[PDB]
Every structure is written in C-alpha cells, then in structure tokens.
Image: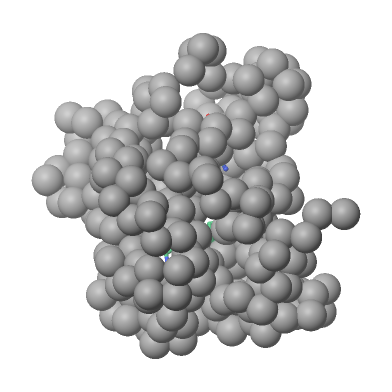
Length: 260
Ligand SMILES: NC(=O)[C@H]1CN([C@@H]2O[C@H](COP(=O)(O)OP(=O)(O)OC[C@H]3O[C@@H](n4cnc5c(N)ncnc54)[C@H](OP(=O)(O)O)[C@@H]3O)[C@@H](O)[C@H]2O)CC[C@@H]1[P+](CCC(=O)O)(CCC(=O)O)CCC(=O)O
C-alpha cells in the first residue's frame, strides 16, 4: 500500500470542523500528519478534533477562530507557525445577483476566498522553502472552470486566487514547494444540504427530489464525498506529487463539459 511519505509532518488545515476541510484533515491524519485545525464554532471543532484523534495516531490541535480576519490568522499561525502543509479553505460567498452586491460584499468575498489564502501563503511559504519541502493546497470551486450563475462572488474571488497561485507556484517550484488547487464539483456536505433545501423550496419540489435530480445530471450519477476529496488532497501533499505544481484538479464526476 502507498506510503505518502509525510508521517510526522505538520499541516494547518483551515475551515475543517466539517465538510471538505474535515475530509482533508482526516486524510492527512490517516497518513501520520500532525494537525492544527481551524473553524469558528468551538463545540463542533472540538468534537471533530476528538474524532480525528481517536481514529489516528497524530496530534490534533483545535483553534477556534475566524480565519478571514487578522486576529484569526494570527491565532492559527501562533498555534502552527511552521507548517509543512497548508490547506486553504473558508466559507464560500453568498448567492445572489451582482446588482445587490455592494463594494463591501465584494471585499468580503475577496478577503475570505482570495486574500486570506494569499496571506497564509505569505506567512508560511518561506519556512517551507527554507526546509526544502512544502505543500499548499487551496480548496476553490468548479466555478473557476465554469462560472456558477448565482455565485458571481465566487466566480470572481476564486478566479483571482487561481491567477495568483499560477504565478507563485512557478516562482517557488525550485525549492521543493508545490502549490495546487482542488476544485470541487457538487459534494455531499452540510452546506449543500442547506443550499438544496432553499433551492427546492423556491422550485416547488422536495429536497430529496432535487438532490436526486442533481445527482442524475452529473455524469457519474452521484455527489462527491468528503473522504475522496481528502484522499486527493493527501496525494497532492505526498512525496509522490513533487512534480505537480500550479495545477487545478477538478473533482466533479465529469460535470464540467470542457475538454480542458
Ligand atoms: N460542497 C460543495 O459542493 C462545494 C463547496 N465549495 C466550497 O468549499 C468550501 C468548504 O465548503 P463545504 O465543506 O461544503 O462547507 P461546510 O459547511 O460543510 O464546512 C465549512 C467548514 O468551514 C468552517 N468555516 C467556515 N467559515 C469559516 C471561517 N471564516 N473561519 C474558519 N472556519 C470557517 C466551518 O465551520 P464554522 O466556522 O464553525 O462555521 C466548517 O467547518 C467552501 O468555500 C465552499 O463554498 C466549493 C464547491 C462546491 P459548490 C457547488 C459546485 C458545483 O456544483 O459544481 C460552489 C461554491 C462556490 O463556488 O463558492 C457549493 C454551492 C453552494 O454552497 O450552494
């Protein structure tokens, strides 16, 4: 079986008490990576930390903070000053029409889903370079490959992060650091349960009916799972992915129709 070669390393995993971030944390812990996990809500984060500790043989430190604020980033970096692995993630922006998005709505989305990842990279990449090993994985969205009609804030902010990452990945590649993006299609998380319920109500169908329709519309016929998302993250973080950088890995069951 495949030794990812990262046992004993340390990962800062953002926005990881639930969903895709949690799947990444669990996958890294299963490969022996010590974790600092961040989310805003203490009780949920502490329960996730307990669950990961019990199922793995690694240290798990929970930091309850808002990763999109200076104080939150300072708290995360105080707990994890020199990570080998950084998984960037935060809550996504709200849906709507851009006629309703103030300058401050745009700034909030840019801060959460573009500038916060850039700042955490700025704070951690030189330590990785100095050690000759680093892995940075940004959780973005299929929206960067095909815009989502109601998510202009994501289409914009996450494409901005993607362009920045394209440049930085190539600049730091000679020092054993890779920077890649993981782009989820439709994944079976609590966030999607909330979205589907609101969409089903607006459409006059049941949420179970809408979920089944959305699954059938995806070529694979199902939603993605946090476990398989985390497995791809773990592979990117491994000693077997050192020649992969600046890449946008789309996990979507074939939903995006572009050849590239
Ligand atoms: N599932 C999914 O399908 C997706 C998830 N997405 C993003 O990936 C992040 C994680 O998303 P997911 O893991 O699903 O969210 P979940 O709620 O389960 O977990 C969140 C954890 O983050 C903690 N947390 C939140 N905020 C902070 C903070 N400020 N500080 C610290 N921790 C924080 C929180 O904890 P708290 O802080 O305590 O609240 C939880 O621990 C996310 O950016 C999402 O947008 C990417 C793609 C898809 P799409 C459908 C794409 C297609 O169809 O092709 C497009 C979304 C977009 O383009 O924007 C969802 C569409 C919709 O939503 O209608």
